[PDB]
Amino acid sequence: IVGGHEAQPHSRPYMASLQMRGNPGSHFCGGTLIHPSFVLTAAHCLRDIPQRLVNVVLGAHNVRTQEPTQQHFSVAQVFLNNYDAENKLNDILLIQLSSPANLSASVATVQLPQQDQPVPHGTQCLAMGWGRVGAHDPPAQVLQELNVTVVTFFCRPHNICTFVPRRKAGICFGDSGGPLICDGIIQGIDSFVIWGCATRLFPDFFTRVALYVDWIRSTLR
Amino acid sequence: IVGGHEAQPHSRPYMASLQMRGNPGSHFCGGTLIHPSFVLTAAHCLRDIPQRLVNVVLGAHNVRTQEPTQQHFSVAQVFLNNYDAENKLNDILLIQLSSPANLSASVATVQLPQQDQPVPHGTQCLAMGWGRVGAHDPPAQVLQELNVTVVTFFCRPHNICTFVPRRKAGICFGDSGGPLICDGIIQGIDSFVIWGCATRLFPDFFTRVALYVDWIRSTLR
Amino acid sequence: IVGGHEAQPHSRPYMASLQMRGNPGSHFCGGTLIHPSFVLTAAHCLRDIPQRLVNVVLGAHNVRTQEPTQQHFSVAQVFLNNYDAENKLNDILLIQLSSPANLSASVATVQLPQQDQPVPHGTQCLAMGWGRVGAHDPPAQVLQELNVTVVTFFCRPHNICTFVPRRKAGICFGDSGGPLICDGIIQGIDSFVIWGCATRLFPDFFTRVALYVDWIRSTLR
Amino acid sequence: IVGGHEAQPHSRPYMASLQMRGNPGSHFCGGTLIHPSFVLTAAHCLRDIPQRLVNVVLGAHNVRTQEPTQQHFSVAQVFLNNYDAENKLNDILLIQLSSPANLSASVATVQLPQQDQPVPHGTQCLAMGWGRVGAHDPPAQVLQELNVTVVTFFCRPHNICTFVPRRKAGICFGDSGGPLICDGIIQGIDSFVIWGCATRLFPDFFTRVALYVDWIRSTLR
Ligand SMILES: *[C@@H]1O[C@H](CO[C@@H]2O[C@@H](C)[C@@H](O)[C@@H](O)[C@@H]2O)[C@@H](O)[C@H](O)[C@H]1NC(C)=O
Ligand SMILES: *[C@@H]1O[C@H](CO[C@@H]2O[C@@H](C)[C@@H](O)[C@@H](O)[C@@H]2O)[C@@H](O)[C@H](O)[C@H]1NC(C)=O
Ligand SMILES: *[C@@H]1O[C@H](CO[C@@H]2O[C@@H](C)[C@@H](O)[C@@H](O)[C@@H]2O)[C@@H](O)[C@H](O)[C@H]1NC(C)=O
Ligand SMILES: *[C@@H]1O[C@H](CO[C@@H]2O[C@@H](C)[C@@H](O)[C@@H](O)[C@@H]2O)[C@@H](O)[C@H](O)[C@H]1NC(C)=O
């Protein structure tokens, strides 16, 4: 997250760090705990990488630290919904944890939107993540969050776009798969930026979760 | 103006219509009365037209008629400031009328902003003109106006960009030179569009008047 | 024509200069004599301007001067093939002169291609016209010509694109309606530029004449 | 490489495969052996990863396999030349191998350009790599090659751009750091693509090797 700020530690307990097994703090994407056993993330995060190498780390703040709150899981399975990499469509992935998370103080779930639920232009949401804090600066130890506004410009109905007009801010690399929080509900998943991070020229793109509620529910059976 | 609405007759008494001398109703550009003997417009409106052929019409609503409210002037002198046509910078030109306007109801001046005064993203403005009301039928007989919002997306600081979020709307051919009125002050001048009118993807560009306030005033003295 | 060079006088006898009647030298668009009574041009050239005020000048070289070689015609009739000004499609118009030109060394026709005849990438053509020589010097007096090559980049099959790979060159304002001749056949009509003239970043766009050949021939009755 | 073809085995012996140390066939970037101890790559290849985890494989063809031609190296040091991740500038990195390669039949160096040496629009080159070869097809097993043409359209001088005129083809993910070979000389390094691979809209961008010729020389010795 570029130009956002440090979240209160564990203030967003549904936050998941996707890392590589055996290399702690090797965060490469965010995810969102939607069920004790399912992390919701971006389909693009899981490409370039075999499942077995994946490590879902829950209840963290500082991912490159051995927090007592941290809980680790490996991937039992993953489900996709016609992800189009060329068009950057359906960039959504449900990861089934090896084991169910222990829903504690620093580890919680979040509500899904209603199927086809709208997020209007002007909606203020929170975007968070451990991603790059500026395209030329070493990653973020601590979870960062950023208030953004849903915009319709330079956007596709497929996605939800956000923008920070006032300042140089937005999602960056590492933020992929993270959640976009609007009124306590996850409305988006970090999908893509254009050209770069915080260009101040285009919105940041998020997968529109409401499109896939029915699928997610049926997938959780 | 695309997707705009007709202004109330003479509600915008500072609206000037640049016409071709000897051809009544030959509106090609808009302009703004800011001093009884000076019209402000875009440098680009007088690229391919010699000074002497310019007829500045004040007091209009329906420019395709000789309204009693009108007052016509020829051009005395024109002033510019480092206009760059390839980069589309400093698209500003001051036309000193052949004679002072006689301020009445239908003809009146507008105030200039202060030098380097800012116009933030989200600032609600008004655009107006007699440009094409679309690329599907002729330009506007009567003055059209459009409520727009200043945006900074896909924009450049030198310019003020606007955009109308919901619908197919924006400035078009013939609106070039007219004012961008924000809080009853002129903050911009219709300078350029990208590709076409009301692309719904690109914002409309305007010269940022606050940059040239000192030059303008200095010239008016 | 930016970065072009002056043509040898009357070495392109099918070059038409479109002007405002009564106002000599007022070249505003190009044309191409393809028949004694027919000038082929871009539909956008006569968008605003009424037919009555247009003056078709043939036999010119320096359009800004009276030349014994020139022949003026008025617009008898104009033909359109479904011009889409927003998509910039079918930018072609047939102007029927009020009287047949008198073909000479200085005034001759140019042949059309066959319907759907391709013009492959790499194809070397000539573009010419009296348009702006760069938006820095006031418009071409004498005919300017430029060596260009057809390209498929950043293009549309509906159009024919050209680019001058090694120099800041290209068609400019005033060249619209002019011819793109390849192998002494007219293959395009100067239709539009992207951003401005000679961007060195976008190919110039031309109406693909081979697309409207039957319509054309038939219109010639 | 998208729409490219399989290079003949060991026909491009200066090709390097940057992989994750301890992860056999974990190819993430290309490189070019320009000296027995130095591999040429893109600076963005070693952004995410730390150098103590980088495995530099020579003499390869199928990267997934344990081939008898492969020589594996470790990163001894790295060199940068003012890399700009914001603007994607100076995307060049010199890697010092822990040990010199044994210049054999399947492992050889490639010649460098002269400093400031031009590569004109129209120059035909070879781009090769083991990157993704199709958005839903994995990354290449075996070395892929593609003839591409150097273009100046939609480009900047800092970069060398290329395009394959009429075919969905070009570089792709995992092609980064690889070389652009023209007339048997390395002229570019795969830097970036715009939006995606083989959009057929934008050129692929390569680091312009000749700008850094002098820096690579002194750094080598
Ligand atoms: C920034 O957002 C803060 C939290 O946002 C609210 O809670 C998050 C989780 C979302 O559900 C979001 O939709 C809500 O607005 C707010 O307390 C705060 O008002 C915002 N900050 C400012 C100064 O804009
Ligand atoms: C549209 O704008 C109307 C007028 O705008 C106000 O006055 C103009 C001249 C400007 O100075 C502008 O900055 C002001 O907002 C408003 O009465 C109206 O609220 C706006 N309409 C809507 C429905 O958005
Ligand atoms: C430029 O082109 C000259 C003329 O081009 C040819 O003739 C014109 C009328 C067209 O029909 C065109 O398609 C033909 O290519 C050539 O004689 C000349 O050598 C060319 N010069 C360079 C420097 O390219
Ligand atoms: C594609 O390129 C093949 C080899 O390219 C030539 O040598 C390489 C190593 C480069 O240095 C390049 O500049 C040279 O052109 C050719 O054998 C093949 O003919 C090429 N294809 C085409 C369409 O000509």
Image: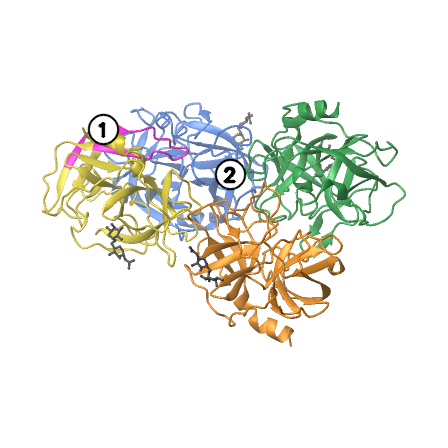
Chain colours: A orange, B yellow, C blue, D green
Badge 1 amino acid: Ser
Q: Residue at the far front: name it.
A: A68
Q: Residue furthest right?
A: D68
Q: Identify the mark at residue C203; answer none if there is no mark.
A: 2
Image location (x, y in percent) of residue B181:
26, 47
* Nearest the eye: D51 or C90: D51
* Residue indicated by mark 1: B218
Tell me where residue C191 appears, x and y as whole percent: 43, 42
Q: Quadrant for residue B20, please give it.
A: top left
- In front of the other: B176 or D166: B176
* Residue C221 can be seen, yes or no: no
Image depth: mark 2 or mark 1 in front: 1
Q: Is residue D66 left or right of residue D51?
A: right
Task: Give the residue at the far bottom of this rendering.
Answer: A221
Of B124 and C93, nearer the camera is: B124
Magenta region includes residue A91: no
Magenta span covers which residues?
B73-95
Instruction: Please indicate whether residue C43 sits to the left or right of residue B40 in the image.
Output: right
- In the picture, which quadrant includes the C terminus of chain B? top left
Task: Identify residue type, mark 2.
Answer: Pro
- Quarter containing ligand 4? top right
For the residue pair A171 and C165, the one nearer the viewer reads as A171
Q: Any atom of ligand 3 within 8 Å of the CB at mark 2?
A: no
> Which chain contains the residue that carries disc 1?
B
How far across and how far down the image is residue B126, in percent?
28, 50
The quarter of the picture where residue C175 lies is top left
Q: Secondary structure at mark 1?
A: helix
